[PDB]
Amino acid sequence: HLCEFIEDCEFTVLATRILHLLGQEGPKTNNPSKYIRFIYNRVVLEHEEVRAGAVSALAKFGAQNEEMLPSILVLLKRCVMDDDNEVRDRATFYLNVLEQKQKALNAGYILN
Amino acid sequence: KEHPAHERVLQDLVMDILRVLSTPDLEVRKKTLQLALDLVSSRNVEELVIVLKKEVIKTNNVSEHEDTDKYRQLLVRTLHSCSVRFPDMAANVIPVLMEFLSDSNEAAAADVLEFVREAIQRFDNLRMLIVEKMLEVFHAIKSVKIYRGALWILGEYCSTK
């Protein structure tokens, strides 16, 4: 309900809060395809900023992986990628950051 | 124009004609600009450029742009193209300056466009000055646009360690 409605019940501000929370929660509650499905959408919206949250939430999530995620988790960041300079940069950088640590290690430091 | 035997001169006479444009009507003007761009094998250029600069001054003036603004953007496009081909010069520096003066996004977008481009183009030298120029501009200024500007530039970085 939240997901859907909020989508078409708007307000960016809400998203900030919820994002943050969601950010922690991920794969302890599974339903991956859906959740992904959502996540993509959330990003769908413009705003470098709106887009950005899906990646950040993801870090706790990614790290944990779910009912299918690690392989693919690795595949995805690749599949979804962006320019728009500082938006480019965000993709690049997260990557670059990613680039910079053994992704397993990477996850551990950053997450905390 | 498909008199592709296309004589030198003719291209050249344009400016004269173009002068008339100062008695505006953008829409007409606009048609001109496209038209204009074409002839230049990166030449009859300077005289023009100069003239452009004249335009530029003219553009300053006191203005109450409403139509001409548009023109400016266009001009810049028209202008942009040339440069690609050309080796260009001080004139260009001036845009940079000019741009600093200005206050609306579309230009920033162009600028940015330039950011991109230039990032590709790198013969560099100019940039550095400009970067300096910019440094001034920057010091000299505040805004989201700027704020954004900083970001990329910052991103870019080099010397004066």
Image: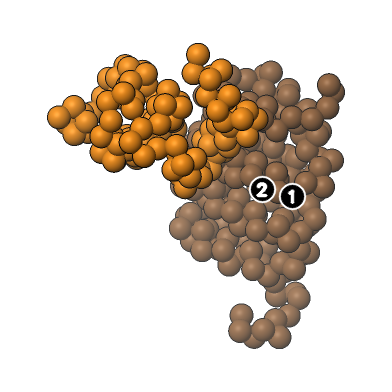
Mark 2 belongs to which amino acid? Arg
Disc 1/disc 2 C-alpha distance (Å): 6 Å
Q: Residue at x 81, y 42 (%)?
A: B124
| Depth order, front residue of A9/A74 | A74
Q: How is the image coloured?
A: by chain
- Asked whether, in this view, residue A48 is left or right of residue A34, the answer is right
Q: Quadrant of residue A9?
A: top left
Q: Is the N terminus of chain B in the top left, top right, bottom left or bottom right quadrant?
A: bottom right
- Give the amino acid type for the residue marked by disc 1 in the picture: Gln
Q: Which chain is brown?
A: B
Q: Within the image, what quadrant is residue B57 found in?
A: top right
Q: Position of residue A16 (x, y in %)?
A: 34, 20
Coordinates of residue B120 in the picture (x, y in percent): 70, 48
Instruction: Residue B121: give its label.
Output: 1
Q: Which element type, helix, strand or loop, lies under badge 2?
A: helix
Asked if marks 1 and 2 touch (Cβ < 8 Å), the reply is yes
B20 vs B87, nearest the viewer: B87
Task: State the image quarter where residue B41 is shown.
Answer: bottom right
**Is A5 placed above or below B140 here?**
below
Chain identifier for the orange-coloured part of the image? A
Q: What residue is disc 2 on?
A: B117
Q: Nearer the viewer, residue A96 or B83?
A: A96
Q: Is residue A79 visible?
A: yes
